[PDB]
Image (cartoon, rainbow, N blue to C red):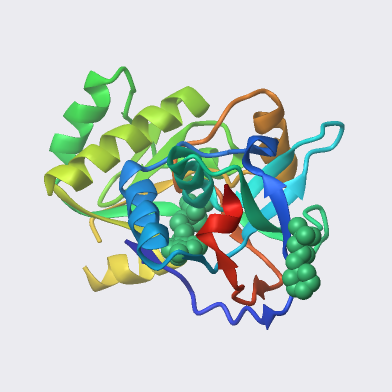
Amino acid sequence: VEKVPKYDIPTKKVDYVFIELDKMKPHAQLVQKELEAFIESVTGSGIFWKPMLLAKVPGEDMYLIVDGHHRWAGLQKLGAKRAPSVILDYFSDDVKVYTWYPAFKGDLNEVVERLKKEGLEVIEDPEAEEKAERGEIAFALVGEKSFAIPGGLEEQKKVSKVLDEMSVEGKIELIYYGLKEDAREDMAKGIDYVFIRKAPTKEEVMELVKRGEVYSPKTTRHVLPFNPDKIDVKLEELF
Ligand SMILES: Nc1ncnc2c1ncn2[C@@H]1O[C@H](COP(=O)(O)OP(=O)(O)O)[C@@H](O)[C@H]1O
């Protein structure tokens, strides 16, 4: 579930280009539920109406998937070969990369035991949010108390893996907030805990994919200068 801060992003009529799926590099782990929903949707209508958003990888004949992991992964699993895509000026100042702030209403202790059991630490720390925003720890866990979860990407992934299982189990009301202050505004209405990491930079996203590595789901949150207008492409054109 997603809460976004009413971003008036303009639709623009930008033409698409067909790009081969094997030229596209993911930056996030897939979510099988989203992959599955896309497969049902595209095979149902037979129309692919929403182009990929790509960025050229410097120094490679490859493209970063900015938006479209489950379209990409879904087309591949169907045996398709290309997707209509819009190529972004990614390093333009007009493109911004934020993160998501996974927040939860629910009980802290079940989450701690599940986090601790995967090898993560949860040390109580009133500078945890400050450390996390500087990128010094993996996550700050902020509710009634503040806790630091140390480490880097490996630890962040473990945290995401645990949260998604407990969202699957129904032990928390997992909402990914676009902005953490909206998680704190809703927190004051009386959310329980909010996870905060430093946002990825564009440069880090590109580095990670050149390494053949990926983030957890809901790590990047791109704010773009436009949404492409809808397109008229038949599924059969993609094979
Ligand atoms: N028939 C379709 N053609 C093209 N896109 C579709 C179709 N049905 C659903 N979608 C889109 O596929 C997307 C699935 O998520 P996607 O953007 O690929 O992953 P992520 O945003 O995590 O990179 C959704 O935006 C959804 O609206």
At x 44%, y 43%, the residue is: 78
- Left or right: 222, with 157 as reference point: right
Residue that lies at the very extreme toward the right in this rendered image:
59
- Left or right: 238, with 193 as reference point: right
Q: Is residue 152 visible?
A: no
**Quadrant of the frame with the N terminus:** bottom left
Q: Position of residue 229 (x, y in %)?
A: 64, 77
Residue that lies at the very extreme toward the top in this rendered image:
119
- Give above or below for 153 relative to 110: above
- Left or right: 7, with 84 as reference point: left
- Give above or below for 145 relative to 207: below
Report which quarter residue 175 is drawn in: bottom left
How many discs appear? 0
- Give above or below for 95 relative to 189: above
At x 43%, y 25%, the residue is: 155
Report which quarter residue 45 is drawn in: bottom left
Q: Position of residue 96 (x, y in %)?
A: 69, 59
At x 68%, y 57%, the residue is: 85
At x 41%, y 69%, the residue is: 182
- Left or right: 213, with 145 as reference point: right
Q: Position of residue 180 (x, y in %)?
A: 45, 60
Using the image as rendered, state which of residue 122 and residue 104 is in the foreground.
104
Using the image as rendered, state which of residue 177 and residue 169 is in the foreground.
169
Using the image as rendered, state which of residue 50 and residue 66 is in the foreground.
50
